Figure 1 (cartoon, rainbow, N blue to C red):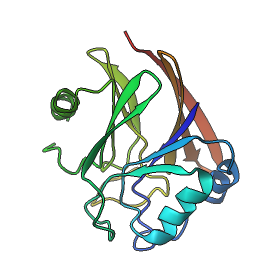
Figure 2: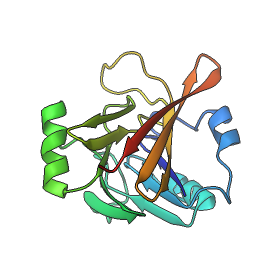
Figure 3: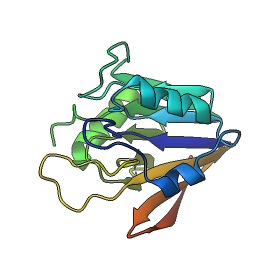
Figure 4: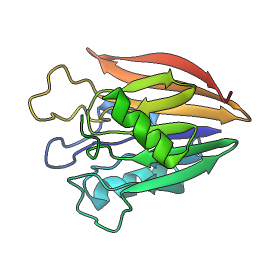
Amino acid sequence: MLVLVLGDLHIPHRCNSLPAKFKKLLVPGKIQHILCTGNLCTKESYDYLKTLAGDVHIVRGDFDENLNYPEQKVVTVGQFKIGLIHGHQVIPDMASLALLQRQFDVDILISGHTHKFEAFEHENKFYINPGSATGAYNALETNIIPSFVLMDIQASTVVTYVYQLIGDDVKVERIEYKKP
C-alpha cells in the first residue's frame, strides 16, 4: 500500500505552496497513509494532507503552530514499525540517526529538518528523509530542491520513490529495502 512521506513545507512563512507539478501528482484515492515530519506550519497545510488521505500522522517540527503534536511517534504499516521525528533534535549526522533508530527500535526511521532528502540502508535498518516538499530555505543551506517520498509497503518489502523537482521536471529515484 501507498504511504506518502513529506514535511518541512513552511507554508506560509517561507513558501506559499507546493510546486504545481507536485500538486498535479498528489490526488485523493491513491494514498493510504501519510507520515509527515512536521513544519507545516499551519492548519491550511494539515487540511490539504487530509484531502489526500484520511490517515494522517504528523510530528511536531520546531516551527509548528499546532502544539498538540507529539515530538516522536512509531507507526506500524504491514510488517514495518516506522519511527517518525522532525529531527531538529539530532545534535548534528549518521551516528545520531542510528542512536534514534535504536532508541525507537524501528525498521525504518523517518526524519526531516535538513531540507535534503535521504533514503539509504545502514546496519540493515532503513532511513528516509523526504526533504522539503516546497523546497523551503533552511538557515544558510544551499542547493535546496523540493522533494517528497512515496513508499509502497507490502509484506516484508518496501520500495521507496523520491520525487524531486529538478529544474522544471519531476525526477524519481527508487530504493529498495527488505526487512532482513
